[PDB]
Image (cartoon, rainbow, N blue to C red; front, side):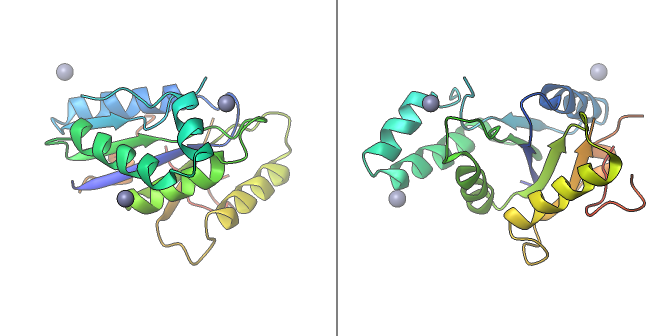
Length: 173
Ligand SMILES: [Zn+2]
Ligand SMILES: [Zn+2]
Ligand SMILES: [Zn+2]
């Protein structure tokens, strides 16, 4: 209602749950009504099963899929003031994962926040992946790209955990 933020988890273990848990706690302390919406499960409405999503995509019913996601979004965010949307991890088996992430963010008019893990990267290698990730969601054109997490309420209030100088995106938390 007041702020829709979609977390794009760009890694098989980037601590997406830790980020969401921190947002739940920050909002509860401020009395802000928060809904965490996970449109699709990653193997008033549960996350859609991946096999159901694949069946709708297989049968050329992507429109039906998006309608169901939008309907579930509304059933799950009634009277929410902040909505945190949990996106899909791009895994080996699913070539539709990142296109579905973009389509969901676009349809929900969500601000996009990428959740990364440093892993083995050097600082500059991580920043290269951050810039690559931003360009793949529209780059400088897409005004909804909001920031990156590496591990109307202000983002500092939403992502309070309490490379930010040279990062391609503002680093949150
Ligand atoms: Zn409390
Ligand atoms: Zn699958
Ligand atoms: Zn339709």
